[PDB]
Amino acid sequence: KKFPEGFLWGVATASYQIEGSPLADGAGMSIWHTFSHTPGNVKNGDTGDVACDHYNRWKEDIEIIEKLGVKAYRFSISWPRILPEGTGRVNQKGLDFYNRIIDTLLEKGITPFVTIYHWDLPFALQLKGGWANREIADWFAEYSRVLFENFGDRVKNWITLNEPWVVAIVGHLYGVHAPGMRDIYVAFRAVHNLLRAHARAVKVFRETVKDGKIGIVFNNGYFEPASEKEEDIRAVRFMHQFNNYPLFLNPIYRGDYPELVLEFAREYLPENYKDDMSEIQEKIDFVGLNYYSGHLVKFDPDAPAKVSFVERDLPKTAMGWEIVPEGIYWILKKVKEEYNPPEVYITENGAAFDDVVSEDGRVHDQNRIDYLKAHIGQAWKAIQEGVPLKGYFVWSLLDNFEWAEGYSKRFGIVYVDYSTQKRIVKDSGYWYSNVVKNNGLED
Ligand SMILES: OC[C@H]1ONC[C@@H](O)[C@@H]1O
């Protein structure tokens, strides 16, 4: 199964998950700093204080990417390293950190994909309401503009937001991610502001980087119905419209939220939200889709949104996520069918397994090889049926801080021994390196 000429094989990380040294060199606090330093928020009190120490070990890590012959690296920039107070003052040492990474990658022929926002909002902006405040569209545009002015001569591939559904709903409704709120009205104003801020950033990108491309990344699940009942099929319709790309792409491409999202959430959205839609339709260059698992879904009259998940005894990862490789083909087809974006990337796909270093000094993660191979094959399929998939990114290069799970979930194709900071390329890493070299699968 060979991929198109020029297909980008990548690996992906995020600033707070790997860097450590959150307050180094004049950096401002982030909301993940204050959230993880609040007892009870993160499994066994884990924080991003040290993480993978990538803040110091960045050169070695890139050298690993090079040695694996991986062609593209998706990483994110810590907003508070660049603007410690969120707006105003620019921190040169913050710029220098990412300049060195950028220059290094280009020297080695690796393509940088920069995620502008992967969840580490400056604490100083959270004090002014964060994603709840309409003014964040201005704050975000200013931050984006600084990035473009400083890095846009070298970085040509940009992503505004990582998984804005998670940012809004997990952060502001479920309260399990920073800033840790549980208010459905705040959560939907966050959804809306994330859109407005994304669109402002695209608009300034067009004034600042006349040769680049910019897009946005969404999380997606593969939802199937529990039965053939009408109501279960509809529960699936709502879950795709709410949890997957349509919550955002329907505004971007059609100028309104999806119909089942409005049925559920119109009372929570700002009163004149439609006034912002023509601006939200700012043209984007690509869609990034993240994908991990599938979910059986059932109408449920008692559930908060009239939907419950139902367990299936399929193979699961350490996260307890059902392994459903056909979901990545489905989401790929669906996105072309619904919005026909000109380019698509799988910006994250991967798995967490309970990896051990064997006596042989190796990490035999056949379970992860099997997971990757299966999904890469289904992505291959989608390409054969005309989906303009331009790239595929494994989450993650490294084992890292898995948010509220802390270090207990390992997604890397490279093992990190946190006691020593030693990297050990896993079997899956060697395997993936062979698929990049061959531009696809042997089977
Ligand atoms: O849960 C796995 C990944 O999902 N997408 C966002 C990442 O930061 C996260 O680690």
Image (tube, rainbow, N blue to C red):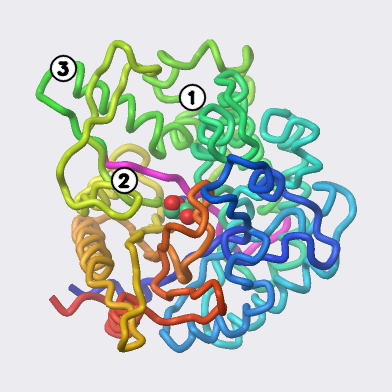
Image height of 174 relative to 154, above or below? above
Quick check: marks 1 and 2 in contact, CB under 8 Å?
no
Q: Nearer the viewer, residue 312 or 234?
A: 312
Q: Is residue 286 visible?
A: no
**Image disc number at residue 114:** none
- The secondary structure type at the circle numbered 3 is helix
Separation of residues labelled 3 and 1 (CA atoms) = 25 Å
Q: Position of residue 407 (x, y in %)?
A: 50, 59
Quick check: is 211 in the magenta stretch?
yes
Say if disc 1 is inside 8 Å of ligand 1.
Answer: no
Name the residue rendered at 17%, 39% in the picture.
Answer: 312
Q: Is residue 233 visible?
A: yes
The amino acid beneath tag 3 is Glu
Separation of residues labelled 2 and 3 (CA atoms) = 25 Å
Count neighbours of disc 2 (C-alpha within 10 A) and say few if under 14, some if 14 to 19, many if 20 or more.
some
Q: Position of residue 43 (x, y in %)?
A: 52, 48
Q: Residue furthest right?
A: 89
- In the picture, which quadrant includes the N terminus? bottom left
Circle nearer the N terminus (3, 1): 3
In the image, the segment drawn in magenta is 208-222
The mark tally for this picture is 3
Dividing the picture into quadrants, the one containing residue 273 is top right
Q: Nearer the viewer, residue 366 or 206?
A: 366
Quick check: marks 2 and 3 in contact, CB under 8 Å?
no
Residue pointed to by mark 1: 256
Circle nearer the N terminus (2, 3): 3
Residue pointed to by mark 2: 336
**Image disc number at residue 230:** 3
Name the residue rendered at 54%, 86% in the picture.
Answer: 63
The amino acid beneath tag 1 is Asp
* Chief secondary structure of the magenta portion: strand
Circle nearer the N terminus (1, 2): 1
